[PDB]
Amino acid sequence: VSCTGSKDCYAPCRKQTGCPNAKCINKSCKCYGC
Image (cartoon, rainbow, N blue to C red; front, side):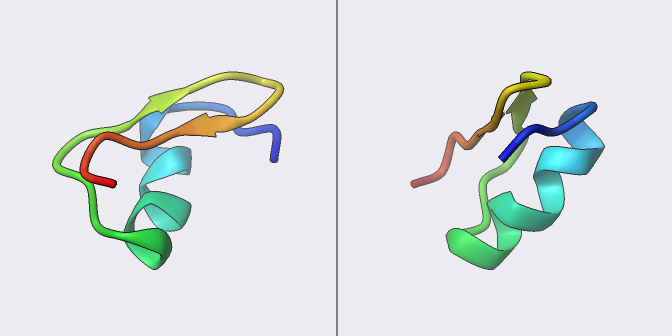
C-alpha cells in the first residue's frame, strides 16, 4: 500500500485504528496506534 508521507499514511492509519502519528514508505504505510 505504497504511500508518500506521514499525512498520506494518516488516512489508512485512521481508517484502520487511529494512530497518533504515522510513518510512511513508498512501498507501504506504517501505523503506531494499532
